[PDB]
Length: 274
Image (cartoon, rainbow, N blue to C red):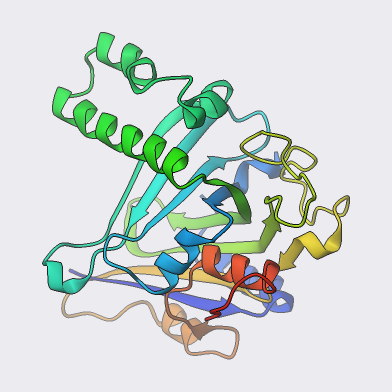
């Protein structure tokens, strides 16, 4: 079989109609469970933003992500690294999990790499080479956090719903809704975070009505992702071809939420905008 993954933008007010159509064909796989929140880090010079915008060889993006509501304790510390084609290497994404109570301390170097990985080394369930890999990752994140004086700058939030028939991978779909960016920085003298890795005056309670609305960017689209596995040489189901060819959706290229968030919410601060 051949794979295809495609993303489409959807007008917000077509969401219900779109979900109804999908549900005729694929079933859905508290309301807070569907939340995905990521806190992107950068510094006062927006060094990481510019590095990612320009696609510098080696340009890193750093974000801390959690799935679900505010009782979720597992925080994923994530780093993306851009590699230019000329290197012969592919860009990479990597992450490791941390309990929430260790996040501030880890980022500050008060909770050490050895401490992060002590228990997983003790249980020896993970191959040591993988643990080594994760240690190099954690150390390098800790280092850039300090060296580049990074702090929380923008949050991305959205809800993800997935639709899938068990045992049939011909078509799998996800729908991301409530796409939102929220300021996390202190650049205007407003201390949004009070030394924490994320602001705590909101949770996953979109659309965050309690906040200063200038801190919020509500994205004007939802995102549909369709993944196909098509036996060569058959066709994808007719209903999918019809849907994707309809007025309800439009194909879109790769779009950075980090870049969109900074460029939109801190427009007065950037001197290059996509």
